[PDB]
Amino acid sequence: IHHHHHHMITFIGHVSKDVNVVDGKREIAYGGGVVMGAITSSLLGVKTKVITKCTREDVSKFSFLRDNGVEVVFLKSPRTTSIENRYTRESFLISAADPFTESDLAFIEGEAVHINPLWYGEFPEDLIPVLRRKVMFLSADAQGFVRVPENEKLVYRDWEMKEKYLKYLDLFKVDSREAETLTGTNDLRESCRIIRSFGAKIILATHASGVIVFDGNFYEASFRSWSLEGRTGRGDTCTAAFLVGFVFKKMSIEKATKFAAAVTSVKMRHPGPLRREDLEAIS
């Protein structure tokens, strides 16, 4: 049964009960960055596994993954992560599932692993070198290292030990807010230069209209959505599509960048994750 499939990806991250509150009204969604990413890679034709944590009670509320062929390991936790977005936007970590540990890493499978955390502390930075030993292609999302809970409010703080750990990642993903926090500039291109100087050999940077990938040179592609509703999940969709194109389909870095943008645009035509009905529109 296990470790017969190198041609696969594992995402590690907490699923989440997300609560959006817009001028009074509460709206509950089940997701967390891993859900969006894993559905994307699966639908794109890469066998996908997720390692997450939540309560036993909440397992069924995240059945969408398994109802789509994604293998999920729901590790035990007395709490489920829950984030309240109060809308400029403030986010609050109402509840936090337990952090990942070294023994949780035993469940990884495949040639690639994406560290996809929601808050700083979820995936301890000292597990990065450990995971590096086990996996051929290792990527992470900056959100897990710069979004720090301070009395439940999630605030952007620099990743103090970034220069110790960035060298162990084949790819590091940042959005616009995270990039300035790490670099001190809003020039996203210069942020890529700086972050590369801290040790990241490939950087994928998303902004509101597109993606910029940097390996010493820049590769850019734009994307579009139909409506506001379509934009949520943009970053995770783009990251996963890039990993599929680059690692699994063996596209050049340029073609993978364009592929990632195209996948993100087709998904942004509607709310929620990429659908089977969308795949036709990618090319």
Image: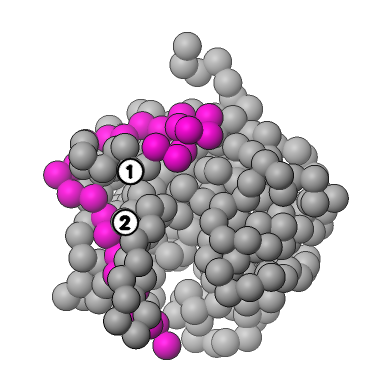
Name which of mark 1 and mark 2 comes first in the sequence.
Answer: 2
The reply to whether the magenta stretch includes residue 82 is yes
Dot 2 alpha-carbon crowd within 10 angstroms: few under 14, some 14 to 19, many 20 or more = many
Task: Tally the numbered discs.
Answer: 2
Q: Residue at x 32, y 76 (%)?
A: 25
SS of the residue at dot 2? strand
In the image: residue 237, left or right of residue 164: right
Marks 1 and 2, how far apart at CA = 9 Å
Residue 272 figure quarter: bottom right
Residue 86 figure quarter: bottom left
- Residue type of the residue flagged with mark 1: Lys
Q: Nearer the viewer, mark 1 or mark 2?
A: 1
Above/below status of 6 relative to 133: above
Pick whichever, 233 or 211, lies toward us.
Answer: 233
Q: Residue furthest front?
A: 25
Pick whichever, 33 or 136, lies toward us.
Answer: 33
- Name the residue beneath numbered marker 2: 17
Relative image position of residue 71 (x, y in whole percent): 46, 29
Q: Residue at x 72, y 57 (%)?
A: 266
Dot 1 alpha-carbon crowd within 10 angstroms: few under 14, some 14 to 19, many 20 or more = few
- Name the residue beneath numbered marker 1: 61
Magenta-highlighted residues? 63-90
**Can see residue 124?**
yes
Circles 1 and 2: CB distance less than 8 Å? yes
Relative image position of residue 192 (x, y in whole percent): 62, 73
Pick whichever, 63 or 16, lies toward us.
Answer: 63
Pick whichever, 183 or 106, lies toward us.
Answer: 106
Q: Residue at x 66, y 50 (%)?
A: 241
SS of the residue at dot 1? helix
- Residue type of the residue flagged with mark 2: Lys
In the image: residue 103, left or right of residue 22: left
